[PDB]
Image (cartoon, rainbow, N blue to C red; front, top):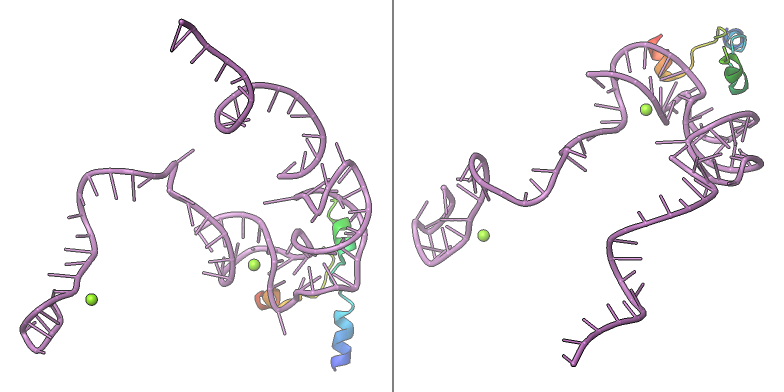
Length: 41
RNA sequence: GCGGCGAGCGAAGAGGGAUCCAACUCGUUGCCGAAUCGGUUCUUAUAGGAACUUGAGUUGUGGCAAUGGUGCAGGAAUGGUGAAA
Ligand SMILES: [Mg+2]
Ligand SMILES: [Mg+2]
C-alpha cells in the first residue's frame, strides 16, 4: 500500500527551482510538503 | 520601612532637570511557501543586481498584516604658513 502511495506522490512533484522561476515570467498541481503547509491543509 | 526594633540600615512613586526629530526585531497568529540562504560566474561589485548551482533549507529560509560601482567636488578637521613696535 505504501509503495503505491509514494509512487503517487512522485507523480505530483513540486516544481524545481529551475522551472519555478521559468513559470513566473507570466502552479502545476503538486503534493503539499512541509509541516507548516501540511498542517494547514 | 528593616532591625538582638539595639548598634544600626533604609528606599520608591511623584516633582524640577539632563537625554531624547528613540525606538525596533523575532517567535507566534493569519495569508503565501524557497520567493531564502551558501557557493560559482557576471557585470569596473565576496551589490540587498543577474545567471547559475542540491549545496544548506520545508524537522521552515523568507516576504506581507496584525543598494552596490564609479565620478567630481566643497566643508569640517587636523596640520603647513603667517603681522607691530
Ligand atoms: Mg545594607
Ligand atoms: Mg520565519
